[PDB]
Image (tube, coloured by chain):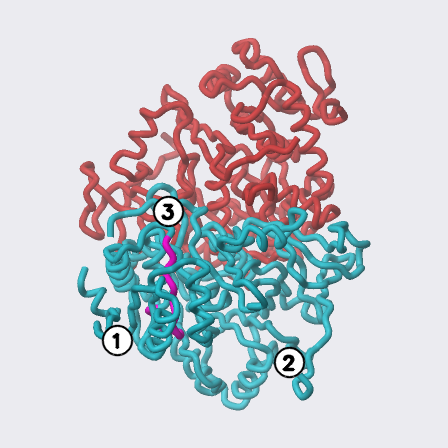
Chain colours: A cyan, B red
Amino acid sequence: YLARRQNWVNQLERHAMMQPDAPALRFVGNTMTWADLRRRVAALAGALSGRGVGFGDRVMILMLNRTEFVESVLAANMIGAIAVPLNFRLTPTEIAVLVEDCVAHVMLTEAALAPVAIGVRNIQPLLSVIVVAGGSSQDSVFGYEDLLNEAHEPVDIPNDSPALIMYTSGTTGRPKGAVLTHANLTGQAMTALYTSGANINSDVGFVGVPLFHIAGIGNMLTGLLLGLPTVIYPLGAFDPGQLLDVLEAEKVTGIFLVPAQWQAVCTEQQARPRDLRLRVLSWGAAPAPDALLRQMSATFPETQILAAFGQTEMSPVTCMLLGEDAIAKRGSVGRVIPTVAARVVDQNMNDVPVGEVGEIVYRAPTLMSCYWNNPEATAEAFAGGWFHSGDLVRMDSDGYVWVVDRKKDMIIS
Amino acid sequence: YLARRQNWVNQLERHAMMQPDAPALRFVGNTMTWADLRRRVAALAGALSGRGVGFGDRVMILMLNRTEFVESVLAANMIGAIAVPLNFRLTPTEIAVLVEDCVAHVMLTEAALAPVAIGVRNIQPLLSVIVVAGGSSQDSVFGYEDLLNEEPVDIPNDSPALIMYTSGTTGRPKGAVLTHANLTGQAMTALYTSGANINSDVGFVGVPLFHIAGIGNMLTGLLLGLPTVIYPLGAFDPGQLLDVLEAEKVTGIFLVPAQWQAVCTEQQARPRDLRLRVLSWGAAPAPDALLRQMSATFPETQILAAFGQTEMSPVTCMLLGEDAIAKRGSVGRVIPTVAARVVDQNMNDVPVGEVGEIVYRAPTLMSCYWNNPEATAEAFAGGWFHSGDLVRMDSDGYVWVVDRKKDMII
């Protein structure tokens, strides 16, 4: 915590000092302690620093859910470089376009995705350093474990330093990458603290969405800040019974699922209960029937149920729906969280009458800095001094936000 | 959020916009909404900068538990001035020493303490401005509500917000400088220990607001836009306190173990309809019996005991209720946002489990003793902050502070 910096690199160091043998990460049944994570991170950082990676440089990450993803984000940040996590379903051309946009020379990937990283290099020769998790040093490619075993001088990381470039998936035209600073991420961890709460002694976190997505990386903030372990769940087919078995075994205390998944988990748990430790349940990314919400409360008594709204690559969580208001204000995305300011404006950035439909626009410390090397798109995003969400909403007399939009029919699509 | 700044002045502006008519402060039965609080704070900031006080200047506050205390702190910080809360038990000579150390020229006081402030000005002519809450604009006195009846500033998160002078004052006064980033980080410790319901919570400050434990109890309410009950200083009355906690639907309160004893006996005898969710104790030892009584008297509540917070230090250790009996006598484990070592006189770690001085590294440590680099260097000797508390740390991480009990008869 030297130089009075707050970021998850310093947090990693504090935990390796104060609780080396405590669990940091759980992945397919193995445990990585803080001393182990710090040791590997510092080794990968040294390998990157030795191969030209310096402050401000960009490091691509092309991985599925696995500990080397967390290790790579932290290693890049430890030397003040910017991690750029990639949607692993992108074509080699799509990734090559992103490599040119932020001019990144290093890509940390894994064996399953190593042919894709090879293809990106052949299309965009700006990528010269490919490090493959679970691979060996061969074929003009470095082996991840080889670089760690081949072994960093402290770097002052101001809290306004960019920590991540999160590229948006709209991909309509020119790519747009949201730049998130450590201060941004710290504020987003704060939002998790005053909505979900925390128990420093017993909580165990869980990330089951893709770690490249802002929802995955965001589920790491609590764990890394508070020194609590985080279960990394591998990506794959959804099995409600096996997930419940894992939640039981790992003693997980908070999980996010989409409403469809909660229905499959609730009926599986009601039929054959597991001994769970869930304290908070989270849902979102689709509507939830009023029957399901009451079914979840009945299936998991003594647990609070939350639903966040607003988080994108550019925006943090802006609205929160606590379990109390899931019935009184059903259909709502909740109220604007106390660390975010919002207006409902019209085409000319004038506030619309209270209760009317307009675009909700935000001001907050947890908004993205900018779109990387794109002053035009950044200027439009913050047109009039407020971040334009693109979401048509309506606020009522009680401050509850309702998002208006036409639903999608899958059979027609 | 002018340039992505995080401080309670910006939070106050945010709350006045998103929920102007929501309760901000509660004092002696009266609600002050966020819109009322912002209007008043802005008027006092205008009155201040009308006296030549600007960025970095020090404004002194000599007040009891009263809404104007919070208005004064926010009004000075709104123009970048540094608020210096004063211990109202100090003699006018002692206060004049503090006026000299930080070279303050403005003192915001109240009618009750206004005799003390004039005495300060008779000892120290640097105090050219004395604004009295609850008083008229008489000779050499500015009326608080009269100055309120009569441009934005960029405030970097590392700007000094407060100067908190220590009580010991062994000859030389020492004023701990706390920045807005410092305060933000201290607010975060409350969130991940006590929790927070951003809909139903109602906070409570009953210790003196000038003390760090008092000003600290405001952080959560101003950050999360939740009401805070301000409790007037005076004779302790467990039944009267219980009646207020019931009427205000207070969700969290701090009390000293002796007060918890009286509150538990009253609440068990004549139970009130309370909404308490978290119970905080500290500043004295709590017997095994009292903690069990508190748990029985208030089921469905969490019991917490913080340690370490001083004018210079944040909270550094937390004892959760599940450990108060397992690890009796402990002050808890070091919190996740604080690094600590137990060292001997050569800055070397003592063997684990052995006694040494606990030293701290954390973003929420004080910046410096105001205008005293000698004391600041001694306090940070070796690269770590020296608490002055001798401790040991067991194999599970729990911290035991070693001391000598103070005998009352002697």
Tag 1: Cα neighbours inside 10 Å, few (<14), some, or many (≥20)? Answer: some
Tag 2: Cα neighbours inside 10 Å, few (<14), some, or many (≥20)? Answer: some
Amino acid at the residue labelled 2:
Leu
Q: Which residues are magenta?
A: A57-68
Q: Which mark is residue A157?
A: 3
Which badge, 1 or 2, comes first in the chain's sequence?
A: 1
Name the residue located 39 percent from the left edge and 31 percent from the top edge: B368
Above or below, comparing residue B151 to residue B335 in the picture: above
Amino acid at the residue labelled 1:
Gly
Q: Which mark is residue A135?
A: 1
Tag 3: Cα neighbours inside 10 Å, few (<14), some, or many (≥20)? Answer: many
SS of the residue under disc 2: helix
**Quarter-of-image position of residue B383:** top left
- For the residues marked 3 and 2, what is the alpha-carbon distance in whole angstroms? 45 Å
Instruction: Give the percent coordinates (x, y) of residue A386.
Output: 65, 50
Which residue has dot 2 on it? A292
Q: Chain of mark 2?
A: A
Select label 1 or label 2 by which is in front.
Answer: 1
Instruction: Give the percent coordinates (x, y) of residue A304.
Output: 57, 69
- For the residues marked 1 and 2, what is the alpha-carbon distance in whole angstroms? 45 Å
Instruction: Give the percent coordinates (x, y) of residue B36.
Output: 73, 39
Q: Chain of mark 3?
A: A
- For the residues marked 3 and 1, what is the alpha-carbon distance in whole angstroms? 31 Å
